[PDB]
Image (cartoon, rainbow, N blue to C red):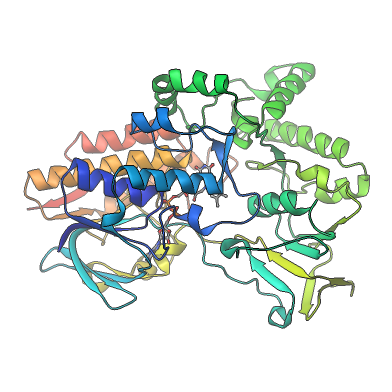
Length: 510
Ligand SMILES: Cc1cc2nc3c(=O)[nH]c(=O)nc-3n(C[C@H](O)[C@H](O)[C@H](O)COP(=O)(O)OP(=O)(O)OC[C@H]3O[C@@H](n4cnc5c(N)ncnc54)[C@H](O)[C@@H]3O)c2cc1C
């Protein structure tokens, strides 16, 4: 028996454990398949792995001593450092004693008679708890790509999601499949280290510089001395990325001024910065979206000296969502040991013992093939497990037509279960979202313990009304199963209205 069981020991699960155990004095256990804390920052050890938000914001804000104590080494934070930070959090707040590592949860069945969750590990261990905190998503299990004969490759075959240790690159011909955010990081990191790099791009995307530089002692002090305000700005923003979020229309200024504004964001770096600090309507106005793209296309044509290679790199879609971020990606393609294959025009048809073969019949001889096809679904990690709520219905079935929730945290027919960083949540920097949700969920659970209620469930009406809110907002924009896209501040307003009005939309049963 526990008051709560938590699944996941990443950002989400760790803070859930801290809040529920230490601030609400609940008896709680957390579980993870991993051998240590860190979540996706434990699993993803691929070359070039790097946060998308700046170091000083990609962290917890609730421990002020930790803010002052923590190293701010570079403007953005590498995977090994995020892992060390989360391990430090675990150290300081004595969290590991309440985490069971190497423990996959196979199933969670809700008991309506006793108003609690039956949780079964993959080693057939059974636990009971009133509440189930799911801090799971969304890192997809290493699915090898569906390519004929992939199993016959005798060289190294690595998936970015399970990057083994001790990989060396020198003297080797290497191929990478995928040019999403993960592929860009790996490609940029390894190109100078391999004998030859072949990039298999199915779909080109725009990338802007991340502009990751070392932070001076003076840079760090500016942040640490003003940390309270820096966080107040996060809570009062849409993205929580530390940006001066623009309301200026792209076409309201001259062509010369517009170039100047894009150029300033380009020099500073950051994907959301280029899209949201420059102007206020890039994700909304077609003309404005095209202007932004043309700025990046022009950069591609300038950096990549071979116009034919520049062309292949240039996305062909009419409108573009957020760009990726890089630390020298387009530069790579000027190298004599790098080949770009457009495998939309010239697809992979087979993989043989020593090569990737494209539809033109060319045998791309490889010593190593890397799958950076980090391809998933937002509710993938919920669907993967056997979760059953009311009348025994599975989450797989309830979401067969797609993930729907109330406030991104509650699923109708699944009482006493609360999602952290689940589907239909806000579009923003993750750790502020996760803090926002963990604190809301805990206050609700605390409310329940204080009013002697043992069953909390979102009504179908609240769920569909959340679906509606998301839809009305989302369809204002060009892009694009909806996130809530009103921003962090408004998401915080939405959930506050719920908690401030007796948790309307929630069935509270004594
Ligand atoms: C390289 C990289 C950079 C990123 N940068 C940013 C960024 O800058 N800003 C941002 O907002 N987001 C970023 N992300 C996205 C990232 O996923 C989130 O920031 C964050 O890691 C989510 O934390 P989480 O605790 O909710 O989930 P995770 O960190 O993924 O941890 C989930 C854990 O739950 C465990 N788990 C799940 N299911 C089960 C089960 N059935 N049994 C047992 N155990 C289980 C998993 O093993 C996993 O350890 C980045 C991702 C990557 C790969």
